[PDB]
Image: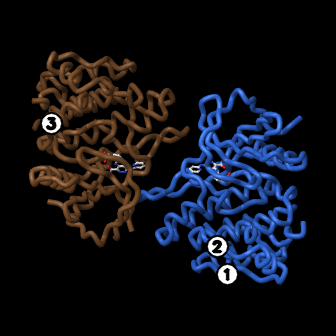
Chain colours: A blue, B brown
Amino acid sequence: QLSFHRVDQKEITQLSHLGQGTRTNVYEGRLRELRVVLKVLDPSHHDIALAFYETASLMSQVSHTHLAFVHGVCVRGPENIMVTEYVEHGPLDVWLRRERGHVPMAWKMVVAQQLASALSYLENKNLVHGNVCGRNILLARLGLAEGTSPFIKLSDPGVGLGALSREERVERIPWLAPECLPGLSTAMDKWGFGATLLEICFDGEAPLQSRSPSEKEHFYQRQHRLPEPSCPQLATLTSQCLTYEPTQRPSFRTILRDLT
Amino acid sequence: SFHRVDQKEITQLSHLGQGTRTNVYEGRLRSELRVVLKVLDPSHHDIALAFYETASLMSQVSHTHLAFVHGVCVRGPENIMVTEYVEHGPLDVWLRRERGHVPMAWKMVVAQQLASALSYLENKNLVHGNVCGRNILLARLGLAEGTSPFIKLSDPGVGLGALSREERVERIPWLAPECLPLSTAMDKWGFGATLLEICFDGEAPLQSRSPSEKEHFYQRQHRLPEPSCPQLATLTSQCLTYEPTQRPSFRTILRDLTR
Ligand SMILES: CNC(=O)c1nnc(Nc2ccccn2)cc1Nc1ccccc1S(C)(=O)=O
Ligand SMILES: CNC(=O)c1nnc(Nc2ccccn2)cc1Nc1ccccc1S(C)(=O)=O
């Protein structure tokens, strides 16, 4: 059977809208009464729902201190709701943009180590995330007080990369690995981790973000490389990760070693 | 007494809440540190003096369970006390959102830590005057499995001696009854009332009840409820007596909390 827990509609209450994901609306919710996040999938075709079920399946089969927990899935007729863990401070990118110019390098290094740690665990299990970006990095603890460190939870990838259109894949540039643009290896999470490091270094302002779909696509087609981070401590690491040859990208074991 | 902070050194951020005659904000202090800014309302010199005395007192103390005071900024008609920022904030708020899921072992650690901070002030013959869950801050939550709490007792804000009868009545049940019409005996009553609030998951007795009712309760010398937790029942009965001399020392309270 299904490799995820089934949630009955009588067990869940839907509350405040928090934002939007790829083909989803995210709400705060209560699970019979635990505070949760409800990822409501748009009215979708069976191939989209199936890519969503695969994400829930994958997440239910994993357990790591830096990966957000999935409670299960609710199928209320034409609607698919993924019931997941609620993370106190929400998306990292939003927070980096609120605190721009006041985020110390030491703090960013802790986030990077924690993210590499979560991705190393998936690598060893030969599991592909497919959507590593600052928006899917959630802050459990901000680490603002003296002698406190940030604590992140990497969210589920949402609707699997394989189910998305070219337009959606182009929207995921620079986080999307270039081998994914035509359209699944763990080598893609190494590019995604690299692009996330740049976004963190540049305080939630990723390269090419303002740039149009045509421009983003043009950049990948012509094999242009992304800027070097302002931070020189992560410059080598991002140059290695952000290569167009997936085999050339280092393992997370090496990345973790290089970070610590 | 206390360090003077120039307005060019601080940055005022989000509003966190309110204290007696103050507005509390998140902030940044250059040499960058995350801080809390306690902005005093436009006030008279006797109110500002009671606020300077608090800053003075809190600059002269050093304990792992007392929040640090960086100094004071004087911006136009506003007196800004620059203090330590604590990660999780007020205990009472946290107890209310986690009601029915706070273990007795956790509450016992908080009680020991609070008695420890108050024992230090008693030995130095220093009065806090505002012991309540709102003034108890969590550096470490301890709510998660395998985490233990770590509290910081905040500064008392505007000293009790500067407040009106109206404000004193609003402080019931934390306010010692001899204060309704300054000794370290008042902090024993305050510690007792805080233990009830902790036991009742941030729901203090008489909280909702009107000023007239609160005042009536003290005037008629009625005693506060026994805590649901039997382990702290004796301790709260001893602390919450109308005779200040009858209240035990923090040395005794601390000793009793180990057993
Ligand atoms: C697995 N858990 C989550 O995904 C999740 N958990 N807690 C959150 N807390 C939270 C606190 C304050 C404000 C907003 N959020 C946000 C979350 N998702 C979220 C929220 C808004 C926009 C997009 C997404 S997402 C990652 O793309 O699903
Ligand atoms: C000495 N330091 C403090 O007093 C203080 N330090 N850190 C805080 N963190 C904090 C984190 C999250 C949410 C709210 N707060 C709150 C604080 N005060 C506070 C905040 C809101 C309401 C009343 C007061 S108070 C005790 O009456 O000053």
| Chain-order first, disc 1 or disc 2 | 2
Labels 1 & 3 near each other (Cβ < 8 A): no
Which amino acid type is shown beneath numbered disc 3?
A: Thr
Instruction: Give the quadrant of the C terminus of chain B.
Output: top left
- Callout 1: few (<14), some (14-19), or many (20+) C-alpha neighbours within 10 Å? some
In the picture, residue A205 is in which quadrant? Answer: bottom right
Q: Chain of mark 3?
A: B
Instruction: Give the quadrant of the N terminus of chain B.
Output: bottom left
- Callout 2: few (<14), some (14-19), or many (20+) C-alpha neighbours within 10 Å? many
**Residue where numbered disc 3 is placed:** B184
Q: Chain of mark 1?
A: A
Tell me which residue sits at (52%, 71%) in the image: A105
Q: Is residue B123 visible?
A: no
Which amino acid type is shown beneath numbered disc 2?
A: Leu
Q: Which mark is residue B78?
A: none
**Residue where numbered disc 1 is placed:** A227
Q: Chain of mark 2?
A: A
Q: Is residue A6 visible?
A: yes
**Residue where numbered disc 2 is placed:** A198
x, y percentage for residue B199? 38, 26
Secondary-structure class at tag 1:
loop
Tell me which residue sits at (61%, 54%) in the image: A138
Identify which residue, A238 or A80, lies in the foreground. A80
Q: Nearer the viewer, mark 2 or mark 3?
A: 2
In the picture, residue B170 is in which quadrant? Answer: top left
Which amino acid type is shown beneath numbered disc 1?
A: Pro
Secondary-structure class at tag 2:
helix
Q: Is residue B51 left or right of residue B97?
A: left
Labels 1 & 2 near each other (Cβ < 8 A): yes
Q: Is residue A195 left or right of residue B193?
A: right
Compute the Cα span from label 1 to label 3.
62 Å
Q: Is residue B78 left or right of residue B152?
A: left
